[PDB]
Image (cartoon, rainbow, N blue to C red; front, side, top):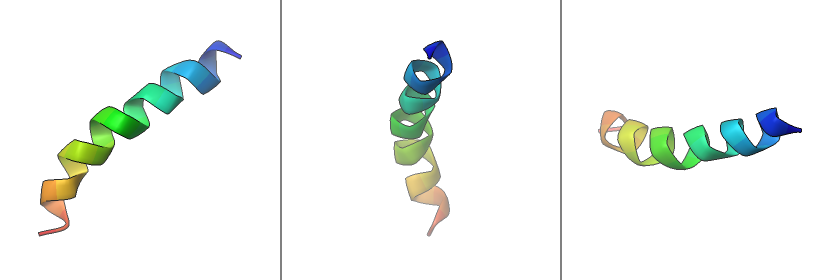
Amino acid sequence: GVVDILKGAAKDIAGHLASKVMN
């Protein structure tokens, strides 16, 4: 289940990062 935790983390990190890409 570690993946769920790790991946769930990338979502928050990559989420904010990719947020600027959408523009």
